[PDB]
Image 1: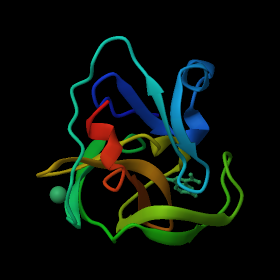
Image 2: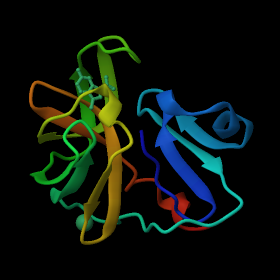
Image 3: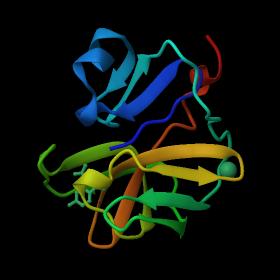
Length: 140
Ligand SMILES: Cn1nc(C(N)=O)c2cc(F)ccc21
Ligand SMILES: [Zn+2]
């Protein structure tokens, strides 16, 4: 699990989104596994506006932050799991690194801030749902 908190917004994997998230929705996309919901108290997080391919992610199935090189956000085939079938997820970034389903929500950060959250992976890969193209998060 895990979320970002850019102001009074909560950014989560679309598949871990709660009833409250859907009952206080802002925007959502199944192909990306992203959903943003409203909050009453503000958050502690800046979103990266950049093309970095280096950063650090949190991996819950190891209790560690790992430094990684990561690919640019693209359309990637990801194998089956408890939450989705074997499909293409868009705006996915692979790094080489350990990941399992429950690692979803872990933050990837670079010098420019929060880059994205863990969304896909397998076979020593990890895909981060990029948030960097979502320029509207910074305001309103
Ligand atoms: C980080 N991660 N997300 C998923 C997923 N959403 O299906 C996944 C599936 C895997 F077999 C291994 C790792 C994974
Ligand atoms: Zn950056």
